[PDB]
Image: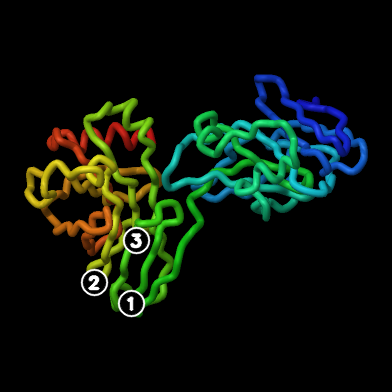
Amino acid sequence: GFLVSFMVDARGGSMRGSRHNGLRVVIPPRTCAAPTRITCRLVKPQKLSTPPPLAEEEGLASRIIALGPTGAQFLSPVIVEIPHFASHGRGDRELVVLRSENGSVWKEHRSRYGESYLDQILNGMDEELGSLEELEKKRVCRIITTDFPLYFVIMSRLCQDYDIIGPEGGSLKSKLVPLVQATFPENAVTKRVKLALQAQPVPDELVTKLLGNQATFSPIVTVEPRRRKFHRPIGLRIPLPPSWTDNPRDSGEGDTTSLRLLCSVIGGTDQAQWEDITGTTKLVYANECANFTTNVSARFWLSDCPRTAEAVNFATLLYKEL
């Protein structure tokens, strides 16, 4: 029941499973000291004595794989690519590699030299590794590891990142988008709380496919958790939609401005109900960003949308596909 079974030595080697399973195992030169039979099999989740203990918004995004020989240790990282079947894209959820040493406990797989070192990990091997963008389009996950645990599986979960802000105030930055920032003044919160500033980039290819050149968008910025009220206004900084940074079609001051500020206050994983709030708040333009305040946590999204009455319809159509 092996998807792949091949001999490998110090020269390295690679193998792909059938097109029906999409597995790719890459063993670079100098990682395997002696001739070794590399294998991979699929594992039925219902056959596990202790399956991954999934929380409410967690799910398995790939098949469970058992790479052989179990317990194999490599001199430097090896690469395993597998397709995922996650039911979402970018947003409130992320994909994480889980591993289990003996089938009893499941933890996040740690890789010290990962995606930032693909070319170095290859050790001169003549193999092509696609970028994270290309893997995203193809719905493929890449596991970089120096050993084979009993099991690997991809899990889908709510983003785990957060920072802590108390009554002294502070600032939050996005992990993905550098200019995305939230400023919490003193007394905005009454105690030390966990907060996250989520910024989801919007790919031009998707916007073009769905809306042509009718609108452009900023990244979607969400102050997490949603459904929270602050005791003082919170400062938010969002990079402008790309067509607006290039050349604004108007001052961005009037209510008929083509630069629309959209807001969604509803709770729920990857749920939004967009409302055009342009003109309800003062926007200050500086450093190729819009700067404004909010008294509540919510999702925020800017759009340079000349057909202004269609901004919510365009946002809704696009958000469904993100």
Relative side of 304 to 270, left or right: left
Q: In the image, residue 145 lies at what x, y percent?
A: 72, 46
Secondary element type, mark 1: loop
Looking at the rendering, which quadrant does residue 26 occupy?
top right
- Which of disc 1 and disc 2 is earlier in sequence? 1
Residue for badge 3: 181
What amino acid does circle 2 point to? Arg
What amino acid does circle 1 point to? Thr
Q: Nearer the viewer, mark 1 or mark 3?
A: 3
Q: Callout 2 environment at 10 Å: few (<14), some (14 to 19), or many (20+)?
A: some
Secondary element type, mark 2: strand
Residue for badge 2: 232
Q: Residue at x 77, y 38 (%)?
A: 28
- Which of disc 3 and disc 1 is earlier in sequence? 3
Furthest residue toward top: 19
Residue for badge 1: 190
As drawn, 120 above or below 230: above
**Do the numbered discs 3 and 2 sit on residues whose CB atoms are within 8 Å?**
no
Q: Callout 3 environment at 10 Å: few (<14), some (14 to 19), or many (20+)?
A: many
What amino acid does circle 3 point to? Gln
